[PDB]
Length: 159
Ligand SMILES: Nc1cccc(Cn2ccc3c4c(N)nc(N)nc4ccc32)c1
Image (cartoon, rainbow, N blue to C red; front, side, top):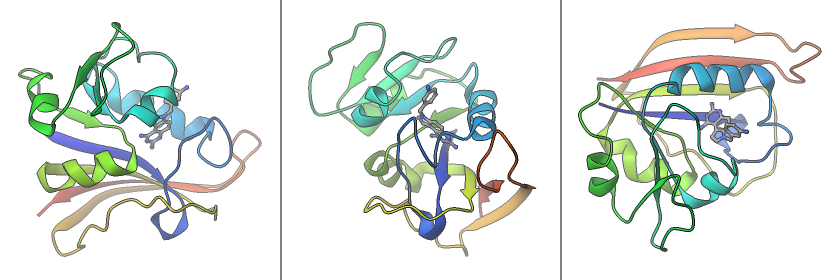
């Protein structure tokens, strides 16, 4: 089954850099744990944003362009991306914006990290009608020395 995992700032703004405010160590650990030993699907910008395949995971890159790295699997369509995962309990879609939009209608689970920050970005996480989604887990954390902003993990399940 298909899950989306994403770090969202206020107004559901999403970005991707090794900088503020999506480089919080605790959001990274959450991300690792929830994607470990699962196939990950991602856009090209997100693939560059990591510069390296994620270990112990099958990495699948959805892009209209041909591939430039043989350590990972390149595909051109949503259904090709899904098939490339094989028979597995959970597929993890890890961004970016356009990829979320494409997989949301087929997703049955959302892993969201709400960061209590504001950053300027045109790229947003797709609007999920809260009538079709049920929150089933929440975990708020205060800012500390390692994590500059407060943050809250949430898991939602499609209703
Ligand atoms: N160095 C590195 C290792 C793993 C991932 C990345 C970039 N990256 C790529 C995706 C993510 C990411 C995500 N999809 N969701 C959440 N909640 N957090 C995330 C944090 C980082 C992400 C960078």
